[PDB]
Image 1: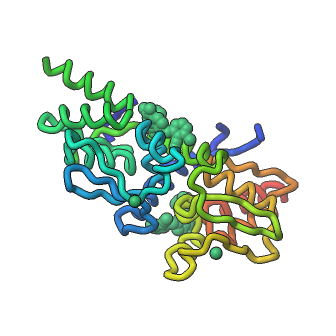
Image 2: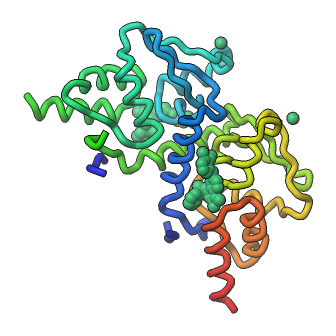
Image 3: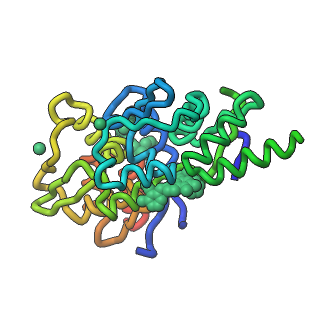
Length: 5
Length: 5
Length: 125
Length: 125
Ligand SMILES: Cn1c(=O)cc(NC(C)(C)c2ncccn2)c2cc(Nc3ccnc(Cl)c3C#N)ccc21
Ligand SMILES: Cn1c(=O)cc(NC(C)(C)c2ncccn2)c2cc(Nc3ccnc(Cl)c3C#N)ccc21
Ligand SMILES: [Cl-]
Ligand SMILES: [Cl-]
């Protein structure tokens, strides 16, 4: 996996 | 885009 | 073949178009009912994203149904958030919805979403 | 919402499952005929990958057809290579098939594939 898009 | 996978 | 070349953005470009088809109600083939709230979708996208929908739409009788009713304990907002995730890769996880999102993901059989919810809850304890 | 988190591999994981459904002939809803060679597929994936199929399946009459016949000049191997690309992001471009792949991509209205074919041909001149 998860990221800040 | 294009790459060698 | 082992000599293929690959277009990095292709899968994301396909998913964007599947969400545009959903927003315009183009070739949607099922209505999911959650406590009298109705959500239109494509069976193939639901199956590709959920262990529960994969089992439902591979059944010889249920594959032909145009309406599927979920358990009355399922929260409509939690379902809406997960349906948006299926079609975009983006999950709207907030303090006020995390418990409902986790319970819905457990029911729908989406393992990585359940694990991420558990980690976010453990960090606030 | 602006507070979303994103799962990097989600779009690729969805596309892999759509190709598994195609390989097992699950919920396929159209046959594409190319010079008497038949290819089973999902209308939503075809529309998401091609300007030609997007126009065909948004038409009020053609959206309901279960069989679509392509122009007799279209090469079946060229079509097969592009159908595999739609479902995997991998394009099997070889010296012996590049001319057929480019002509098929022009017909199907897949711009970036046409451009890549043109660049590969220009490099060998
Ligand atoms: C349990 N589960 C999951 O956690 C998650 C499933 N799908 C997503 C895309 C959310 C995922 N897969 C892997 C890693 C991360 N995320 C999921 C999908 C299915 N369907 C299929 C499985 C096998 N083969 C076919 Cl053809 C389909 C289809 N359509 C089933 C279970 C899933
Ligand atoms: C011309 N063309 C293209 O070169 C390529 C199209 N699709 C792919 C995924 C191959 C692409 N898009 C962008 C960059 C690279 N590759 C393509 C797809 C469509 N369909 C839609 C367009 C707009 N909105 C909706 Cl809902 C759909 C659907 N389904 C049309 C034309 C395309
Ligand atoms: Cl029904
Ligand atoms: Cl027909």
